[PDB]
Amino acid sequence: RTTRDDLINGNSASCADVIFIYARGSTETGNLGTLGPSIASNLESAFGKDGVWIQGVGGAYRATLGDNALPRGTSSAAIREMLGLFQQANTKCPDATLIAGGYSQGAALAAASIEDLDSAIRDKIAGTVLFGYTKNLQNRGRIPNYPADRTKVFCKTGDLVCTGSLIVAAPHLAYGPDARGPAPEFLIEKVRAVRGS
Image (cartoon, rainbow, N blue to C red):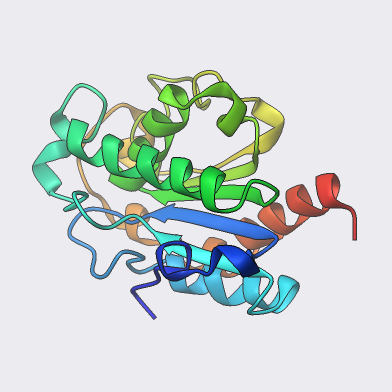
């Protein structure tokens, strides 16, 4: 449900073909929050329970509201935690295709991590989805050092965080439908583009 640690718990001798690393929004529960489970269910339908590992970013990532105001839109501790998960994935399962996503503060965290990532690992992330991307304006809708074709940003009209602000308005909480359909659709398409099927 709201907590998934498939990568950490996963057996290296039986690596999934796809590994999804996801960062929740501020004040959300578990390590998946409100949107992660919906994405997870759909990925499982496409690749099978044994075909995909769902890993939320927990540990040092406390998803503290105040951290949105920090330089990168999240804490240094949180970036360290997500970088460590990508590193663990790369080590435990070198042939797995990676995919990532984040919501709100988690979207900033995802962008910051991917930006700092070793290029050899970053290049393994076939697609990334960002909802209510807090650095959308600042980054011009991109993730630094990461291709636009592998990025999909969901930013609703009226969601002030997508427009350079840190104010939380109603549209910021309306990504449910996106997480249930277009987000996983994008991720599945990007994985199949490289892995075939």
